[PDB]
Image (cartoon, grey):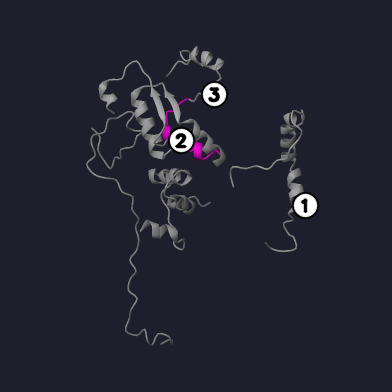
Amino acid sequence: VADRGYGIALQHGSPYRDVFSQRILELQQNGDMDILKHKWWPKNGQCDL
Amino acid sequence: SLQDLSKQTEIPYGTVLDSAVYEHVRMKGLNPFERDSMYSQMWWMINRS
Amino acid sequence: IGISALTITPDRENVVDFTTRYMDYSVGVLLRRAEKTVDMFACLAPFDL
Amino acid sequence: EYDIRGIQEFLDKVSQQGMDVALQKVENNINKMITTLFDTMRIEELNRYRDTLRRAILVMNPATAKSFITEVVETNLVAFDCHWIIINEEINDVDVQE
């Protein structure tokens, strides 16, 4: 679905997010989120959905 | 009718590549602001592979 | 002059000045008729001859 | 054909006042320009792009404006409320009526 992407808050005015965007692009290109997704949504889990 | 053609999928249908009708269906099917959704189904009959 | 099954489309009205149209353009579909379903021996056909 | 050094003291002065001006060239092949939008953007983005088109300025020759308008209005990227300025030095009355 449109309109929405997930996110998490951090204390306002920090340098954190400002420089995290490219690091998130790294984590995307590594598929590190996809490793976490396989962990948390195992494709061959206990049941066929 | 063309509606009754587009509902079923047990007889496949298509058109000549790069024809004006082909590109007209491709244009209709991709436009989300289109009022009549039928073309957005027919395109998935015509775009296969 | 130019004349054939030529269709008025806006991208062509940029370089040639079509007349008023003489007939409408319509998209259609071709099919094969359903033959006929009834025969005099359909009551015996559940057994091979 | 437009030498974009006319609209170059305007794109300056406007940008002191904080308007969100945007450029875009209009292609020689309007239909495939338009469908290259639908084939390559998110539905999340179309619903923002179609919010901009409500107020636009055309700076071009009338025989292209007739073919652009007729293509936008027919594919429903503009509704009953837009406001498009159309500026030129020479529009003859037969195009004012078209």
Give the chain of mark 1. A
Identify the mark at residue C32; answer none if there is no mark: none
Q: Mark 2 points at which residue?
A: D34
Q: What element carries label 1?
A: helix
Q: Amino acid type of disc 2?
A: Ile
Q: Name the residue under label 1.
A: A39
Q: What distance separates the C-alpha of mark 3 from that of mark 1?
A: 44 Å
Q: Which region shows up in magenta?
A: D25-41
Residue most toward the front? A12
Q: How far apart are labels 1 and 2 at the CA level?
A: 42 Å
Q: Residues within 10 Å of mark 1 (few under 14, many from 20)?
A: few
Amino acid found under the numbered disc labelled 3 = Asp
Q: Residue visible at 49% across and 50% down?
A: B47
Q: Subunit of mark 2? A: D
D29 is within the stretch colored magenta: yes
Residue C22 spot, x, y in % from top left = 22, 41
**Amino acid type, mark 1:** Lys
Is D29 on the left or on the right of A28, as rendered? left
